Image (tube, coloured by chain):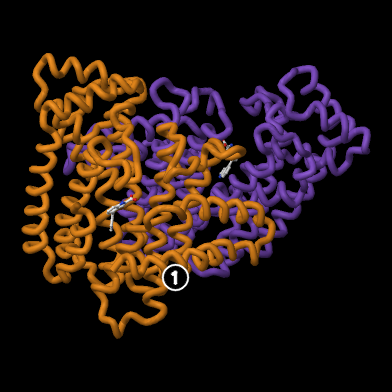
Chain colours: A purple, B orange
Amino acid sequence: VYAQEKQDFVQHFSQIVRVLTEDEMGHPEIGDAIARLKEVLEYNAIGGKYNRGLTVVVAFRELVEPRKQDADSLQRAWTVGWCVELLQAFFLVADDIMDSSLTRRGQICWYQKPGVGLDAINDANLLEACIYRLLKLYCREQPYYLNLIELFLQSSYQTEIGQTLDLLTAPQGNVDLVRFTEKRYKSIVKYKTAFYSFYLPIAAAMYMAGIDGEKEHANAKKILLEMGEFFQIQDDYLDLFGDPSVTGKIGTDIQDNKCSWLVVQCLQRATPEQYQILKENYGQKEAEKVARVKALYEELDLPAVFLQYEEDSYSHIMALIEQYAAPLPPAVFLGLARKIYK
Amino acid sequence: VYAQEKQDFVQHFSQIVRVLTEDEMGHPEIGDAIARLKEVLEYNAIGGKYNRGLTVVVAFRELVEPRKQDADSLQRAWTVGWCVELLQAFFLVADDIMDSSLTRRGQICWYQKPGVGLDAINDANLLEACIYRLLKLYCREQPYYLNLIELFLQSSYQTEIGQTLDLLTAPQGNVDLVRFTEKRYKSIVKYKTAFYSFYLPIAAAMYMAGIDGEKEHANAKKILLEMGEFFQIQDDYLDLFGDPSVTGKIGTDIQDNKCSWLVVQCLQRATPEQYQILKENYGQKEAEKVARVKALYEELDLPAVFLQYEEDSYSHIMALIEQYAAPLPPAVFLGLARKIYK
Ligand SMILES: O=C(O)c1cc2c(-c3cccc4[nH]ccc34)cccc2[nH]1
Ligand SMILES: O=C(O)c1cc2c(-c3cccc4[nH]ccc34)cccc2[nH]1
């Protein structure tokens, strides 16, 4: 469903850019600013998997009657999908600055580019501003206009709350495993990742479909927030125990003192002696010390604890879909679950 | 009109904070994040003159029938005023990071506080998020709800475009006076300062009053953008030639290579020889070199050029009010003009 649509979705970015840089036509005074906005969009919104944005298009196709899927209805779906990608681009540009990252998707972080620096704070704000410009240009006259504006604003706020919670839990220069609890971990995931990655794209498609009822959204939110929790737990597991060939990424979470699912479980299972070993090696760059944590996790059989959690989670999500999908087609959630699991 | 109201406006901040930190009641998982949000609001939204926020309250009182100014109508006016102050707080926190500032209103910039740093990027985003949270909490059921959401979003976008234009014109490490033109200067002022400082607070009061017509807003915008241009030109003049006792501030614009109105005029009047002297001394910290530019400005009689510009501007604004205030009470604009001029 995603692999087919990917092409039409990615092809729509050129229109998105044209429409956003068409501001220059009526006002050539701001041309230089608009030229810069084009660079920011082209560097930061391109090069990812587009999964979150594609979820909007896929869910729109499964929620709306095919006879109501005219040229313009699909044009708005592609735009709302691109808005999800612009919300993400805004968060990533800013997160890379805050955590002093070097690369993003194997390429140099926008702020690390010569002549950019802390100016990327304004660039990230412009990416955020584009969402609302696009919603106005494409959805101003639609009955769900306000619903979409509120959903993007609430998604921004939850993610920012999640980011605060995260920054409070793992300060740069503070190696305290006492604040690394399961309850705290689950809260960071819900707010920082699960709302915008899973709930936002389905809820956007739902409003575009005329499904605006609090019950339906509460039901969809219950499935999606649980999918978001597994997604991140899996991401924290794959970070260390995942093969770097298949994943296309190499693990760093231990070196960065992250409130990872792996450390949360380790802390729950470590004896006072085992706690001390983790208290020393966690947060250090050295390949000998990083090897010690991997060995401690392996010793506490966390890959098995994960394998069990994965089976329990899939079972739970299927019961969740069964109980809360109606009146939405279960295939809306089954599509995501197939992609997230294994 | 401002001095009376200031007290009721500032007293409303405690309610604003209570209402914004009441999120913690239903969700104690995010309590730590909410505690941090309270600190950000209390440090960054307090300590200024509140002029922009007060303009909302003053204009609301002059545009709405006193019989329609019930307890709740004034409660919403105070909140919308505080939203203007939160939009400003968001821009200042971010601008201080981008231009590496040390102090703001004689106190240490939020990002410069120990244990804050680049985390202030998220804090600035939260300040921005609060506007929309307050508009929802107070104005959700009002007919101008969407009008206010769009106005704040468009004000954010114009300011960000203005900031880009500014960052492009004066790069940190690039002393090029060729890009410092009057047309560019006027564009930076319109976008970065005039829209949110003058148009936004009057337009907010106008929508709350039921005045939503494009004509009325276009007419109000014509006066307000010209007031915003004089305000900044005056600010650039006072920066150097203003008495630091009366102003309560000391000049730094020359040291920072700012696209100031003073340099724009200097460049328009400087001979090829005079251009070279400015080409050397502008952007340097040294008190001997800073004294050389002040002397060059004085030699080119820029304080007189300003004095003439000020009289021409006041004359123009009064003709503007006369031609474009109707059907609004001219006292809405006359109040601002009295405050801006002298
Ligand atoms: O970050 C990535 O590159 C990435 C995302 C994802 C997702 C994913 C995440 C959020 C919403 C989704 N909807 C549809 C897929 C998906 C799933 C699998 C691998 C993935 N890799
Ligand atoms: O920045 C300051 O401290 C400051 C603002 C101002 C303003 C001002 C600016 C924008 C909108 C306004 N509405 C009402 C007043 C006002 C005017 C005079 C001195 C000032 N000092």
Q: Quadrant of residue B267?
A: top left
Percent x, y of residue A255: 71, 27
Q: Is residue B78 above or below residue B171?
A: below
Q: Is residue B147 above or below residue A173?
A: below
Chain of the residue under the numbered disc 1 shown in the image: B
Percent x, y of residue A41: 38, 35
Per the image, the residue denoted by label 1 is B138
Closest to the observer, B38 or B25:
B38
Q: Amino acid at mark 1?
A: Tyr
Regarding residue A35, the answer to whether it shows in the image is yes
Quadrant of the image for the C terminus of chain A? top right
Give the crowd class for mark 1: few <14, some 14-19, many >=20 residues within 10 Å: some
Residue pictured at 13% horizontal, 65% vertical: B325
Q: Is residue A20 left or right of residue A151?
A: left
- Count numbered badges in the picture: 1
Q: Quadrant of residue B59?
A: bottom left
Q: Is residue B213 above or below residue A288?
A: below
Regarding residue A86, the answer to whether it shows in the image is no
Q: Is residue A106 above or below residue A214?
A: above
**SS type, badge 1:** helix
The residue positioned farthest toward the front in the image shown: B245
Q: Is residue B295 left or right of residue B151?
A: left
Residue pictured at 31% horizontal, 82% vertical: B68
Closest to the observer, B209 or A46:
B209
Q: Is residue B63 left or right of residue A61?
A: left
Q: Quadrant of residue B315?
A: bottom left
Percent x, y of residue A221: 60, 59
Q: Quadrant of ligand 1?
A: top right
